[PDB]
Length: 280
Image 1 (cartoon, rainbow, N blue to C red):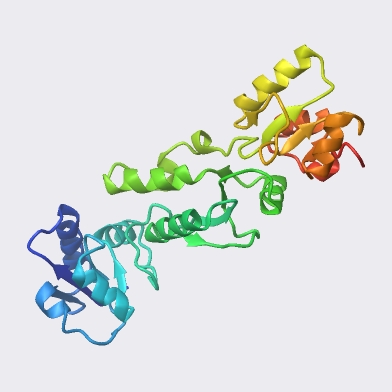
Image 2: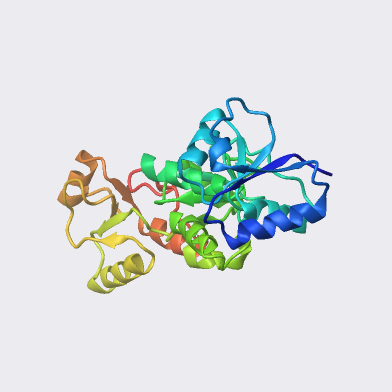
């Protein structure tokens, strides 16, 4: 099923561009096809709903068409769509490739800037972003453990990955080494069980203490030998007693039992503290 498309031609044009140009010539009549210059591209004043192919996604031409609201994609989306015999994306925002097509991302515990950056990569790669969780969300991107969104996602067993997964999909796909998101190993970017947690303990024997410390670092958290202000996030403590316990209560640090920590390691995700409060 054919579509109108304008290839934007600059002096320096990528191999990928010319390959898309040829497959398009082959795929449909040259009626739906137009090749334009940087020169004329600039005189376009309205969005005519046709598809534009630009490479790279920068320069003054790109900025112009983008500002007009044009539907722009990189040669790669066209190549991929003709190979899998699917339709070109709507491209409300520019789409550079289809590496993440059919991925639907939600985010939690990221800095604002970092969330924005992640949204943009996913969109550039033809994925969709869904903030709130439901059955349509395929992957949660988490920068740390413990938010309610993280909890809901872990109980459904959705994958919970780090932003580096996204950034790795991007870089590898820039250097043409990858074509789908399945091409790399998800398990390498799993969010660590204790990422973001800073753990202190009290009332344990030296042996139990050493183990918790080992197992904390192993699972991405930090271990502190003493309770300090605005450092420690969790105090492992069995009984609501004693000066150290009492000071963490004042500071509103989570006081949780030993079982919080071991159920976390065993179930594969940071457990909800309120199930495990030292003082129920």
